[PDB]
Amino acid sequence: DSNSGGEREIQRTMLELLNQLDGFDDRGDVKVIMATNKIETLDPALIRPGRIDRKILFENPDLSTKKKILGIHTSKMNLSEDVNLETLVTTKDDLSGADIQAMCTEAGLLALRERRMQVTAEDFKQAKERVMKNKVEENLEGLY
Amino acid sequence: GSRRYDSRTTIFSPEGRLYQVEYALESISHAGTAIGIMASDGIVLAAERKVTSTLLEQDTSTEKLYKLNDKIAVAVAGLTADAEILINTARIHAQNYLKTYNEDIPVEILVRRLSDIKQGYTQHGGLRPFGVSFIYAGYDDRYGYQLYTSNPSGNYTGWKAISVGANTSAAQTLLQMDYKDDMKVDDAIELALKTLSKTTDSSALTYDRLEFATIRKGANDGEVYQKIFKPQEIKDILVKTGIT
Amino acid sequence: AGYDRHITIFSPEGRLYQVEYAFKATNQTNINSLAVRGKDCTVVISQKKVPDKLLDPTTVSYIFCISRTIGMVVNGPIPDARNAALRAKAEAAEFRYKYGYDMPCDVLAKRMANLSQIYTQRAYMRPLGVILTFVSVDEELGPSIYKTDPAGYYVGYKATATGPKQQEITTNLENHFKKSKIDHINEESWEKVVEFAITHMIDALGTEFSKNDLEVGVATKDKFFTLSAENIEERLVAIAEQD
Amino acid sequence: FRNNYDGDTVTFSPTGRLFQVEYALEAIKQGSVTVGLRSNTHAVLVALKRNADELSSYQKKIIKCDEHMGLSLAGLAPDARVLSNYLRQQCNYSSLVFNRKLAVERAGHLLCDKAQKNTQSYGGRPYGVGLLIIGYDKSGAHLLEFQPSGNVTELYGTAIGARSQGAKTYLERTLDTFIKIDGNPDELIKAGVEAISQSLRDESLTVDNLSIAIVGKDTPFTIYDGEAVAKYI
Amino acid sequence: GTGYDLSNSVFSPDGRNFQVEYAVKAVENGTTSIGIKCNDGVVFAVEKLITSKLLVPQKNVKIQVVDRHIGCVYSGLIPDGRHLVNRGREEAASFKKLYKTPIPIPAFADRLGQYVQAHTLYNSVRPFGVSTIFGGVDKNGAHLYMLEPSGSYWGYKGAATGKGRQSAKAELEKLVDHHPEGLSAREAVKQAAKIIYLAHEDNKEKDFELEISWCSLSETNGLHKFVKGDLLQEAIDFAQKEI
Amino acid sequence: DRGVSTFSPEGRLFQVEYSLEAIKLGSTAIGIATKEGVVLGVEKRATSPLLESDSIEKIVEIDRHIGCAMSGLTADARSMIEHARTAAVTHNLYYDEDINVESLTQSVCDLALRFGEGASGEERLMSRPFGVALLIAGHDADDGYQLFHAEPSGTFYRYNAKAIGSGSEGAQAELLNEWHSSLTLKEAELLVLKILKQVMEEKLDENNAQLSCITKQDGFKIYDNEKTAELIKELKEKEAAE
Amino acid sequence: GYDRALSIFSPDGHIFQVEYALEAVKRGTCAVGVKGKNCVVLGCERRSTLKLQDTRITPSKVSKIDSHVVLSFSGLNADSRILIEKARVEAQSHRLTLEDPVTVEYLTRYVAGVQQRYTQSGGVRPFGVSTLIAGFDPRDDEPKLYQTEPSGIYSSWSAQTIGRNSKTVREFLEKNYDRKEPPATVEECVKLTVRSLLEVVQTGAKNIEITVVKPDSDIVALSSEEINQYVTQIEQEKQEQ
Amino acid sequence: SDPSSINGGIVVAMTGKDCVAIACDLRLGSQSLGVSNKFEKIFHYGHVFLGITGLATDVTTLNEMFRYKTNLYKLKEERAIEPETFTQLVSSSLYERRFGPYFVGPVVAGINSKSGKPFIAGFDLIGCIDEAKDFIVSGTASDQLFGMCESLYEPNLEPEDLFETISQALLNAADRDALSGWGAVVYIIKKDEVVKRYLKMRQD
Amino acid sequence: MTDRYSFSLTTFSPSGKLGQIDYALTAVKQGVTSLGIKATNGVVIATEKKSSSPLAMSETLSKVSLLTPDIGAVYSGMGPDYRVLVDKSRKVAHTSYKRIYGEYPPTKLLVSEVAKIMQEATQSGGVRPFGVSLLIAGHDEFNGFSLYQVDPSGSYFPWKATAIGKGSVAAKTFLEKRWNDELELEDAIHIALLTLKESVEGEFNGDTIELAIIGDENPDLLGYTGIPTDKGPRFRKLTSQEINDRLEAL
């Protein structure tokens, strides 16, 4: 309601960024990297992929990659002897890199309430149930 | 011209999916929650009505459940308007198989004939797909007890425990760990009562907002008995199971 | 998505945009007319406006005859007026052959209203930009006037009117019924009913008309006819003598 | 330009014109050039054939209807075949039902009714190919000029195609010549050769490029191709 | 919103149509045509603008005659003008089949009226951007009508539309005061040629053509035919005398 | 986002203009028509070594004496051949003879532009015109061997040597000086393979190229992989001379 | 009904309704298959996210069109049911009209030919699923494996995969498998498909479905215990080598 | 000339005290040759029984047609169909075909599940509604039943005594036709249970 | 040719709902508010007549129509499409039942047929959904007295008592504490009058309020005698003088 400028702000603001990669002269010291959730809603003419020859996509990691990501967050974390790294990765189903840290953060908050240096195995059981419920919502893809 | 007002219902998106079908799946989350359970001796179906109050008529009504056959039940989760179109055509196609082959229709044939209707609007006709989902449960002497579900996209798969509607992934979490192959009919009722209580938006749980229609097998083998639980019998199982 | 206002669909305000503009099309011609219910009959009057001398006064009329027992007056542009005129004559003929005896007034206003409701609901047809007003004398309820709106909503009126000045004309017909506490004119003769509606129209518009400036329809029991130039001018003679 | 107002076939422009009619009209001006003329007892039709390669052949720009009449096309080739089927159908219709040959005057009205249906209704399109209708009947020789809108007007002679409007200069100064020439079909054919030569720029008239079809009273409609027109070059 | 002028059925916020207004501008871009109504019959006249010398004189007939009793002249797009007569030709053939005796003038106006109305009610078709003037001698008296692109028409003592509509039709008002009692069919032919030259001031930049056709019961007796022989050349010298 | 009947400002249909650009997006089909026969050839353009030589067939058979090749998208080609064989084999039943090559081309090309949305006057259901280019060849008892080209625009020309697809520009101009009216059947086989070898990514073999032939006696015949390999070995001797 | 056209040529010469429909196959379950001299093996995976799915009541991912030939697709499951039903009716219609059992070559060109209609038919949309038809012709032991693309182009392949991670499996089948010397035994054809599923299924069992096609109308579907038997033998020779 | 008399059939319905009894035979032949002795002309719709006599083509075809409408009627209301409503349903099904209709003798007998009053009805080849409080018979061999059921049947009979009354008016009339015989079945319709009994008669 | 629009005007919004049926319910609150109350001895429904012109006749305007003699109906707002739905409902009710089963359909089966017409407008193209909300109330031999709420989206729900319209927020809440298990027909009328009176900001009389009640079978409303089976229709329309008798009764 407030900052809406109509359809005139649409053409002036977007095409201003395109001219910075075209009309604006540079010796090659200026780099422009754009990232977002969905780039399809944006005007494809703004990209002009003669300036940007690199396109990087992203997918969900496999069971082998999640074992390395889990060891990163648990490197500085104190874990008990009954906690297995490969067991937590096996329980991971359709999760991204942020969902792995979400379980490591939730498991730390459970041990923080009881003030435990080494996180026990009971905290990871309640952490994976809260992430898959609220933080992880079923996508609208729905096929298969 | 008619090309400008057309919203292009069925078109392939750059992501490779359909716009109207992707948005129709969200409408299921805005409707009641229907959770089916397939036990060893029968099939237990659960449902919860949306927008209920004291002025509602609890005497005879079923919003989320219907009966398409003597041996086959159905669970309706989605828009009620688009549901009656597929339900009326369901009993027509079910009796046509009984009128010709003179035998009870299984669930696998009944669902695939109804799914082709939903698959038709997603291809031709230039219309919107049905925004209602169904759960088909029936008895058969071929594969035994069969529990299937549908989607606005027109696909059906086998499910031992299925959950649709609001909080889909929240209910399936408790159903996966608590499911057992030896679970009987009585133990399957307690699984649905504990699931619908924690996944709702209210504090307590009454018998006016729930619907349960199971499939029981009597002493005579080969024929089951379709029994829809009346509100008098729904409040009785809540006390025996400790839900209250 | 600016095409929501160009057709008939549910608006975010809960209204219909194309229906609101259908009532505005009747004020393009700016033709004021009214209809009152007499005792044993019904007399309708209309303002006859001829822009150019090349027009034949006998050919130009805003009052059309659907059947012998039913008259009609329509406000707004003539092309949408005569479009529903031939559609109303077809419904009156189908009712005589198939259904039974001659059609009464309420049935003709109801069938033409339901016909416009189908055109309003369906998005590929535009609604009529005119207003259908039917006058006749029924053999049961007696004199009755039914004014069909372009939105497809018909309702009975005691003394109706039309045009942009209708709200100023309605006040004249309303204040007369409040003092006498009567729902119809008690004059039995149809000649006094003609001069009755003309008197209230002149004082409301503040303009003295002529024989070619007005067209007065007269609907009696099982008969309908349109007054000629000599019959309309004869009514204006006794008005100036009495008042 | 492109699509603003009349991009939909049922929309009228604020200037009182139709761009769809103008779009299909420009297709004739950018197409193959052709000329034509007629006399009292005879009518001459001259057309030029082009192609995209020297090794390629030349598609015939003259379609035969019956022995007493013919036509020519300047525009999209397959669009003229559909209109030619409707014209030949009326020739056999009047021959079977009325036992008469289709008149040139009545052929233009029946051809106009085919194009007006696509322009006044959505989903169709006007044919962007021109048709010069030649023929002979008991009244005399008649020539017509077809437009994408369907306008039909009888003329002594005209030209439709690339640089065809500029070639009308020779037809205007000679307008008083060929109309009084009767019984001399050779001179009437050579009159159309000098008219189309005014529009020649890159390539001139050759054996395969020149296509001449003459129709008359004692001489029926005959398409002269190959070396038949080599003597009239 | 935006795009109210795009399609047909979309109404304007004031209750009018843009496509109907755009079709009126197409009428003034064509060749003008006039008409004269008398007691015995009506007289049709049209000025055909000649482009170049390639046109063959007097071999082109713009007026398309319906049966023997109805002539039709149009000013506007030529393709849209021929479709109206072709539609009216089938209506006259369908009428004479069931209804025996030929269709009168005021009856034939309703067939072209409703047919144009259907084109304004659909988004898949466009209205006719041509104004057709038709008339003749009916069973009782005579009548003359001018069909507008909007479908609005009435009885006209005279009808003129085209590039000279502001001129030629303005001279029709002097014809009423010249012969208020009546005008003969023979004199109306010479008066029709003068009106063409009075509006020729805007047509002087090109070459013109005079085509006059009349029908009445005095001479032709219900036969609509063009003027030929010395009668056409006599009206030219009388009209050019005042020029 | 418009109708298929909408005209471009140049006076053409958008469906017609964009259909011609789809020809270069596919394979390259080259053929030469001589007095002793018509030598046609195509390129399979295998993207993987596991593709079978019998998989993609770009040269079909309408009649024993009449044959054609395809290039570009082959989805629209299979539909046209079904109608091409319909307008041919059924025409044999009517007149008890063989249909003319030029007459068969007209019946096939007329099915291109009949598309539309709600076509008045009759029932025509098509979404888009055919985006495939077909080279129609054959032989008769009057005009002789002829090679036509079926365009998506509904027009056709008789080409002595025609190269469509990706070779419609560079490979097309090379056939101007290499063609002669006295070219025989044997010399035309080595001339086509000489052009196909230079326009192909890898070396020329029987798996990546398939050629056919149309004669008066034998009619339509497809060269065997062993027969094609013999012509390729003879081509290497012609490449190295002086 | 709906007469408005959908597929429209892009200014580049392609079609939006085609290329955008091919992305639905790449987002679906990968379907890989190979053919030997005496046998043909078609592997297929399932969705590993969803659980509690009974294998018996769930329809098989490999649809059997005829006794001697089956169909294993990858893509939209909504558009696949239309192709499976119409291919089986034509299989009986071909036996009714010509009194001949269908052939794998005729079945592929029919399914691909029907897809060419919907692309050319105004008012309908192309199929977003790609089918793989493999079987044996009557009185013929020669293996027949044909690919059916959503665009309508069909071709024969010795070893070909479709779906997600297709380019990864295609590069594995070129170097490991040779078309000149195919395996003449059934056991070697089954182990070859399992090796291609190790880089996609990623350590799973119940999500793998392998269908064995044999001549003389012989079809043997490997159970859950039979599939894991070949997986164990390959894993022992994988890490150790 | 008479396709409905080729196979033949018998049907009879009486009324007791809150009880009705419908009966038929087991004989279904073809022309003069008997085929199946195990055939039954009565289908179970629930507490409302409907017998059908006539051409065997129309019998086997309509048995699937009536159950098509009753299943749609029962599943919507979640209750059994009443004989008074089911009567007017049969008349609309047979009248749907005018020049092509089905030739059948159907006679319906049932008891209301609410009011508890016995109701019987019958039809004809065209499906005309026939309602009577004593007995209604139809078919080719019904002609013998009009004389048997008029004298023997009396109003207000006990349910048990009704079986002996309908049996004497059935087996005696079954022997007077060539197409009737090969045993007979009698259905006793009551409010609690339905007794199904077979009759032992001659075989010819 | 005819119409070139074959697509449905109702599409799925990105929020997960249908934009047409969402604004259809809003249009129901843009007009006069109706109501109804179900009791043990009958069903009492009421509405208000809002005259656009002071000279209009309220007798010719009937906001409560009759589908079957035992079942009434009432709408909210002006009801532009109400006349279309009732004309199509009376045809499908007699054709599918009176012309097949020979008897009128019950209350539960009739509301399913009324919603069957409205559910097709939200799917089949060329038309728009119905912006009206009706109330199906009647009596049968099994379900007894029942009142169903017809939503403009095409779905129906049973309700003891409800009020939909401009005052639907306050009127529906007031009926919760005013309803119980044991009620009579005349006792339920006073419940409707106390709630409707607070919602009327204009003239309050019997001519502007149409009160329709469903009682027992009335032999006077039948029209023939001698048949004990049919005792007459249960639905009855109260006159102008009978409504004013209960207005001052409060």
Image: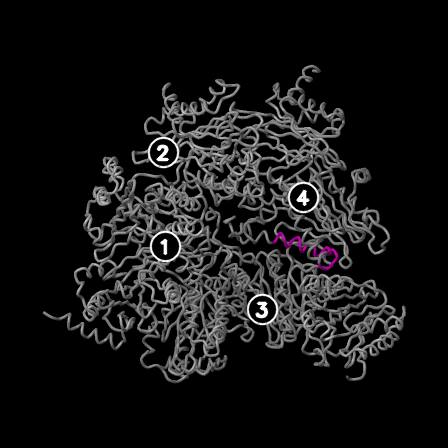
Q: Disc 1 versus disc 2: distance between alpha carbons?
A: 52 Å
Label 1: element kind: loop
Instruction: Select label 2 or label 4 by which is in front.
Output: 2
Total count of labels: 4
The disc placed on residue E231 is none
Query: Residue I29 at x, y = what percent?
Result: 64, 43
**Amino acid at the residue labelled 1:** Ser
Tags 1 and 4 both on a single chain: no
* Vertical order, H13 against C27 (above or below): below
Instruction: Select label 1 or label 4 by which is in front.
Output: 4
Which residue in the structure is indicated by mark 3? Answer: B148
The disc placed on residue G10 is 1
Label 2: element kind: loop
Q: Quadrant of residue G32?
A: bottom left
Tell me if residue F237 can be seen. yes
Tags 3 and 2 both on a single chain: no
Tags 2 and 4 both on a single chain: no
Instruction: Select label 1 or label 3 by which is in front.
Output: 1
**Amino acid at the residue labelled 4:** Phe
* Magenta extent: I100-119
The disc placed on residue E58 is 2
Q: Disc 3 versus disc 2: distance between alpha carbons?
A: 82 Å
Query: Front-most of I84 and C196?
Result: C196
The chain letter for the residue carrying disc 3 is B
**Amino acid at the residue labelled 2:** Gln
Query: Residue D29 at x, y = what percent?
Result: 30, 43
Residue G139 appears left or right of F144: right
Query: Residue F170 at x, y = what percent?
Result: 22, 59
Q: Disc 1 versus disc 3: distance between alpha carbons?
A: 42 Å
Which residue in the structure is indicated by mark 4? Answer: C95
Instruction: Select label 4 or label 3 by which is in front.
Output: 4
